[PDB]
Amino acid sequence: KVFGRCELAAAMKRHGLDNYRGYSLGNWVCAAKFESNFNTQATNRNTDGSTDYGILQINSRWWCNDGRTPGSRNLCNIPCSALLSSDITASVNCAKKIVSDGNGMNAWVAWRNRCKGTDVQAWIRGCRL
Ligand SMILES: [Cl-]
Ligand SMILES: [Cl-]
Ligand code: NA
Ligand SMILES: [Ru+3]
Image: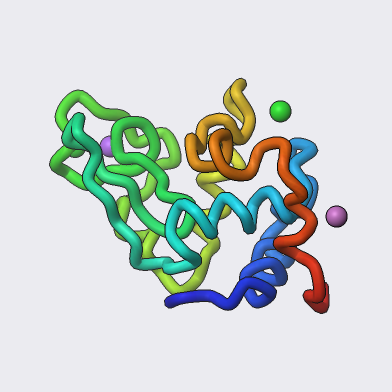
């Protein structure tokens, strides 16, 4: 599923991301924009042999099991394929754990390089929430 900008903002709020660990909703939306272009089915292979999955490109090195990432952890306790679903629950639940683990949203390098410090509120501007 490719979400609409406002459609995702709403979905994210419904699923509890708005201000989760102090990160306003626009942060989450901007991160999803640059990680996956709002496509739940986005996958990208990392040079280390891990893969990133879904709307927030969650990595199989630490967070989900894909069965082909040597020496890796599955800290969110899910198959990485659950992160590709048109239902964002597993993505959101896992993102809450990731953002809680110490570095905040800096875990998402596109967030750090492309969203952090910007007018992230523009990403939710106009949306019925
Ligand atoms: Cl594995
Ligand atoms: Cl933080
Ligand atoms: Na893994
Ligand atoms: Ru503004």
